[PDB]
Image: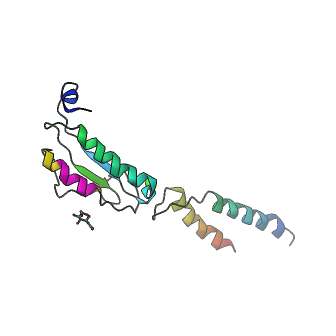
Amino acid sequence: WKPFETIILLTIFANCVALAVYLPMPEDDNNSLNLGLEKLEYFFLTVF
Amino acid sequence: RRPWYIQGAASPKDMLILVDVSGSVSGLTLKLIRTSVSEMLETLSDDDFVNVASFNSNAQDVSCFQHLVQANVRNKKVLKDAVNNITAKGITDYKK
Ligand SMILES: *[C@@H]1O[C@H](CO)[C@@H](O)[C@H](O)[C@H]1NC(C)=O
Ligand SMILES: [Ca+2]
């Protein structure tokens, strides 16, 4: 079916934003957003 | 900042200095706090009380005191050797 262009293109483009606001912190520190998107990295792994 | 100007412009103080020591403070912001704590303790007279408590994952007293000191000349010298050996890693919480 055609709609795999429609879905999974937005799957990547959401996932790169998931790596955009990933804010690195030097000596093992997490703010809140890095805590959340680690669990959201499970969502992107779930799809593929 | 001179002894005679401070007593005549304040009252005694039960003061308590908390130093955030997570991962977010290694580098430039470490050397400043090591400096700025060491400059804060000189504005004390000898009615003022202090105690230095880093907060981290848990909150502890890196001082060997666990309560308030009298802040002599002497007890201010103890804390500065405590301040100048603080590591920096972990997670901020502000609630513990
Ligand atoms: C930190 O340095 C002070 C002063 O030399 C010393 O009393 C203390 O034991 C040191 N702590 C560690 C973990 O090296
Ligand atoms: Ca922090």
Residue B9 is covered by the magenta coloring: no
Q: Residue at position x 17%, y 58% from top?
A: B64
Our reading of the magenta stretch's main secondary structure is: helix
Q: Taking B23 as reference, is B14 above or below it?
A: above
Q: Quadrant of ligand 2?
A: bottom left
Q: Quadrant of the N terminus of chain B?
A: top left
Q: Taking A18 as reference, is B15 above or below it?
A: above
Q: Residue at position x 70%, y 61% from top?
A: A14
Q: Position of residue B11 (x, y in %)?
A: 18, 29
Q: Position of residue B77 (x, y in %)?
A: 19, 51
Q: Nearer the viewer, residue B14 or A21?
A: B14
Q: Position of residue B47 (x, y in %)?
A: 13, 36
Q: Nearer the viewer, residue B49 or A13?
A: B49
Residue B95 at least partly seen:
no
Farthest bottom residue in view: A48
Residue B92 at least partly seen:
yes
Q: How many marks?
A: 0
Farthest front residue in view: B2
Among the 4 quarters of the image, the one containing residue A18: bottom right
Image check: B20 left or right of A24? left
Among the 4 quarters of the image, the one containing residue B82: bottom left
Q: Residue at position x 64%, y 62% from top?
A: A19
Magenta stretch?
Answer: B76-83
Q: How is the image coloured?
A: rainbow
Farthest top residue in view: B8
Q: Nearer the viewer, residue B66 or B39?
A: B39
Image check: B18 left or right of A13? left
Q: Position of residue B14 (x, y in %)?
A: 19, 39
Image check: B37 left or right of B79? right
